[PDB]
Every structure is written in structure tokens, then in C-alpha cells.
Length: 168
Length: 170
Image 1 (cartoon, rainbow over the protein chains, first blue to last red):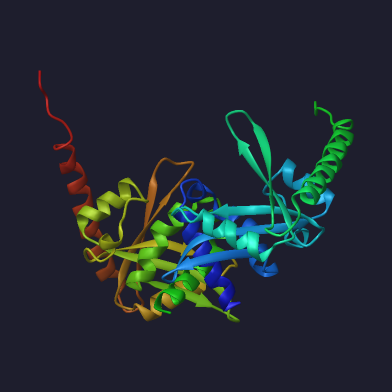
Image 2 (cartoon, chains in turn red, yellow):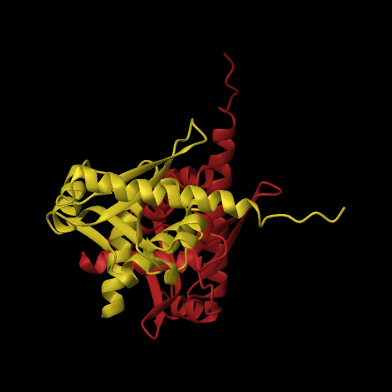
């Protein structure tokens, strides 16, 4: 827990050294980082006692995956262990150390699969990227991803049918 | 470990900002600007209760030049400015769980002979309200004399700065 604050401080410093994250509000740091630390679902790489790279992941059920994709700031701590659909909540390496982070994930989570969303605010389009550990079979990974995707798309479309406009 | 202590303190402060209705909306860049030099210069107080932080304040010891630079842009100070003179300013004051009186008392009793100012920008007014704080062993009459001088020195130099903004070419 003293450890906890120390990690939080490092991550804050690393956000502050990152061109986009430095502009984000402290509310989003608490939302994205406290549960990562509490659940230990993060990797923090350091050099010379300073942080250089950080990624975190939430293990979601489908309900929470849809909630997150509707609003990236909506997860609460309990959601982070709510299922088996893994999402990278943050992935930063502002000083050029991304390959080291990538490798660390590849080797330490060799049979895991993760997705991430990136949003372009000028088109309002979000894209989903896929990542998998270093030992898991390419064909099997690609099939698990296809299944995740089909489940997500089908549930989104179902929810699309109930959507409406609010008017006085 | 000098800087693991540093990160620890920075995390505690960040947590405190995140618990505060206004500070939680401020950016991480402002946290680094306001908090890293406080920690480096040790010009802060962090109150804790049961091993959790509850309140934090920091201060910069400015010269008149940096005071003016700060009041024109509250995010403009750099670390060296924090020890640049004897005009003390509270840079942060946060106590999101209701412990502001406790900070106040701690400062009053532990900095009994010090004077500090703080600026709050209204906001429904476009006016900054400058508040004046003094330690418990400074009497009122004395505090008020020193503050009046600080203020007159600030106002005069703000006016005189206008003369250097522009030249006319015709």
C-alpha cells in the first residue's frame, strides 16, 4: 500500500511525460490506474529508477466490454476481474521503449489474448487491435478473436434495436 | 529511495487530487508542474491519518518578478522559481475529506512567524481574490503592514510593466 502510492506516482509521472496522457484529468488516472494496481494487472518497466513504460489490462465480461466501449471511463474496480475478455486499458512508452514492453507481454503472457481500442476524435471512429502472447498458436488465436468479435458485434446490434432519442 | 519516497509522495498527492471535486478535473501536466518542485524543495506539508494522506499544501518562495509571472499564469513557475525570493505563495491547498481546518492549524502553529498569500480565481467573477495568511505569532497589526507593502509593491510593478509592452513605429 505504500508500494501502491509509489507505483501510482510513477505512473502519474509517466503520464505527465506523455504527449496525450499529460493532458488527461486526474480523475482518469484514478479510474485507469487504481484498479490496475489493486488487481496487479499491469506491467511497469523502469530504467535507472525511473519508469519508462506501462501497460494495464482489465479482464471483462461481455456486459462490461460493451459498457467500456460505450464509455472508456465507465469501468469500476470490480469490473476489472469480471470476465475473461482482456482489454489493455493503458499502453504507454513515451521515451521509445515500446518494443521492450511488447516483448515482456509476449513472453510473460504467452498464451493470453488482449484487445485495445483506439479512437480517432476527428472521425469519431474507434478501432480495435488484437494482441497475443508469444507461444499461442496463430490459428487458434485468430479463431478466438473471431469468436470475441462475433459475440461483441451481435450483442451490439441487439442493443442497437432498443436505442432511442430523448425528447421533452 | 530518495526518489521512491518522491514517487510515493507524488502518488499520495495525485490520489488526493483525484478525490477532490475541482482538482480531479485538472491535468496531469499541472500535477507535475505544481507538485514536483514542492517535493524537491521540501516546501510542502502532507497530513496523514491512519497511514492515508488526507491533506496537502505547498508553497513557493518567490521574488516579485516570479510573483507577477505566476499571477499572470498560474502554471508558469519552474522549479528554480520556488526558492527565488521571500514572497510566499500557497501553490496547492487540498483537503478533500474536510480536513482544511487541520491544515490551517498545522500551518499557523508550525510556521508561526510566516506570511503567505494565495490566489483564487473567482470564477463567476473574472477577479482573483488574493487571500492573506499568517502564522500564529504574527499579530494582526504587523501582518497587515507587511501585506499592505507587498500589495503596493505588486500593484506598482504591474503598472510599470505596461510601459514595456509596446513601441510605436508610426
